[PDB]
Length: 330
Ligand SMILES: Cc1nc2ccccc2c(=O)[nH]1
Ligand code: NI
Ligand code: NI
Image 1: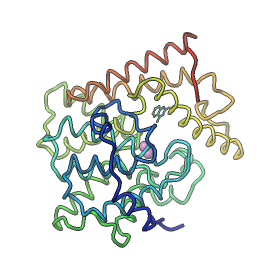
Image 2: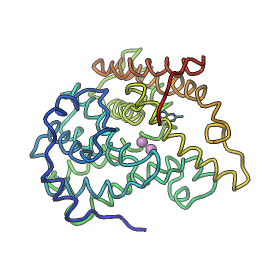
Image 3: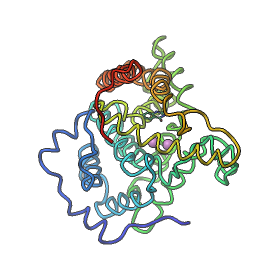
């Protein structure tokens, strides 16, 4: 109930945080894994906003309040949590740095914030579940149910006293950035990814894609959001494999709930069907991840390292299926 608010201790702490010098270089690379640096995660986000958008883009006190309240409105779920938010924000930073001048100052600030906020107040349940069992959220938000909720949570946080990092924008720029953020969060609904990627692929192959056309820009930003949201598949294999354990922990918890409601879950969500997981990952990489990064690389050539890493991880899942896995830790 209600929107959680960080403490004075929390945001003042972030304000005075300084990032270890060695990490500056690392944070620029697509393959950077925030995993080993938990205490630094909020500071890593400040650093990225300051590098991309400038140290004067946001009032520092309001930014620190905003970040630490965002952290507080992520739940202690296995995957759709604070760590995931920062991971997705980092991928976006890396995409923006490599493509900086394709995007406006307003788009860059909106997108970094959209990524940090995009799974706010996630409960560990899928759209499929909410709609199957008529949760109140599915009544309010007939499609893209959780994503409309995450956007609503973002606006709630901005509305807290001293949290509105966008207030200094002109009235027109303020409306524009909230729309950038709304569209970007909604785009993280994978249901919409399939149509979006197909359209972009067609616009690319026929040469009609035009980034001066707002509807095209919106679709490109959409695919960037998918690429950032799925970016665990673009890390080094051990990192990718550990994250997949967290993703499946959520899925199996949801399948357990469906069993109590008299419905057998899809195999992916069935903890008694773990043998099917490697084939399931193959299906997901083939149907979602590989096409996404393929089209993104076509439109934005500097993102190629995401595609190469995704392909390397597909190969690893294939090795699993063939029985060639070596020792793994969890
Ligand atoms: C099935 C599935 N696998 C994933 C692997 C990595 C990142 C995200 C996902 C996901 O959303 N679904
Ligand atoms: Ni989501
Ligand atoms: Ni997400």
